[PDB]
Amino acid sequence: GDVEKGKKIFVQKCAQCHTVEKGGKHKTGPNLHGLFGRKTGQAPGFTYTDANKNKGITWKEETLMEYLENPKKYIPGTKMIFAGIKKKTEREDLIAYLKKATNE
């Protein structure tokens, strides 16, 4: 996938809840400002369900594309009332954009 597509796809899918671009409004999900290497939760300005937080994994491309398929498998109490973006390809676009948003 592609960052430019990832912009669009992020804005379609995630905008409704998140805006991970330069301290955007933690509306229904926070700024995931720097995912790759991050342990779960860590949202002082938008305290997590603790569920997310508690899993305490390491977010990287895989774990992300995985959770974004199947967030409930990862975190049963995931407060992300969401479809699960079945299409690996759509998720790649997102991980790509993450790699120039939630990264550098």
Image (cartoon, helix red, strand yellow):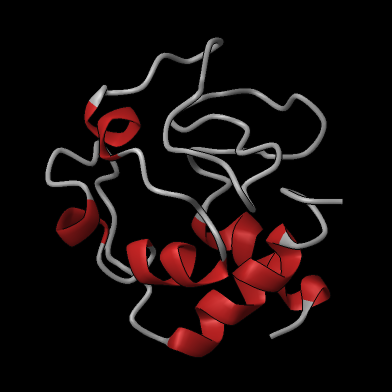
Q: Quadrant of the N terminus?
A: bottom right
Counting the numbered discs, the total is 0
Q: Is residue 14 left or right of residue 97?
A: left
Q: Position of residue 15 (x, y in %)?
A: 58, 46
Q: Is residue 92 left or right of residue 66?
A: right
Along the line of sight, the residue nearer the viewer: 69 or 52: 52
Q: Position of residue 18 (x, y in %)?
A: 56, 38
- Furthest-left residue in view? 76
Q: Position of residue 37 (x, y in %)?
A: 61, 49
Q: Residue at x 69, y 37 (%)?
A: 33
Q: Residue at x 48, y 72 (%)?
A: 62
Q: Is residue 76 left or right of residue 81?
A: left
Q: Residue at x 62, y 59 (%)?
A: 10
Q: Position of residue 103 (x, y in %)?
A: 77, 51
Along the line of sight, the residue nearer the viewer: 27 or 92: 92
Along the line of sight, the residue nearer the viewer: 82 or 63: 63
Q: Residue at x 62, y 47 (%)?
A: 35
